[PDB]
Image (tube, rainbow, N blue to C red; front, side, top):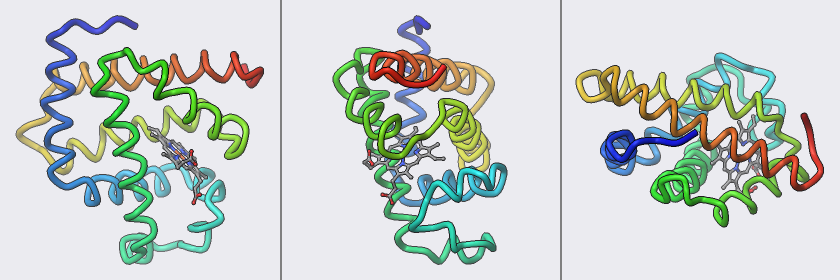
Length: 154
Ligand code: HEM
């Protein structure tokens, strides 16, 4: 809800390792999301036809969308909570057009933490994880509040 400066530094330090391979991370993240919560796949008319993990990894458009996710997320994270203006378009499209429940944001948050562990086994320790979890939570809580402001959910 409020991150210390240290936690924000941890988040941005970790995020710089995402930005080193945005496509790899975004692809993995979407794949983990889709494998651990298949219900989220059917939200994607572009991808709902992808079943095996090998198929999803061969989907360039899935990779492209991973980039879109993470670049949008990274722009938000870099604001260190001052992401009001960056969230509204995301909240708007995910509440009203995509109809994404906040719970689905929790699933992708888990998929982010998981993927960061499997791509950075020595770089993503307990502190960095706590910091990243708090950042994604704040993100999810603020998105929740922006849903409510658009008159949606919860
Ligand atoms: C960190 C969390 C997330 C971020 C930053 C994010 C970001 C974005 C962005 C930038 C777009 C493109 C512009 C737009 O449509 O608003 C998009 C589209 C979309 N998002 Fe998300 N998203 C997140 C979580 C999710 C989750 C968890 C789901 C569903 C389970 C989802 C479903 C969709 C869908 C269906 C689209 C349209 C896809 C398409 O047009 O092919 N999003 N998202």
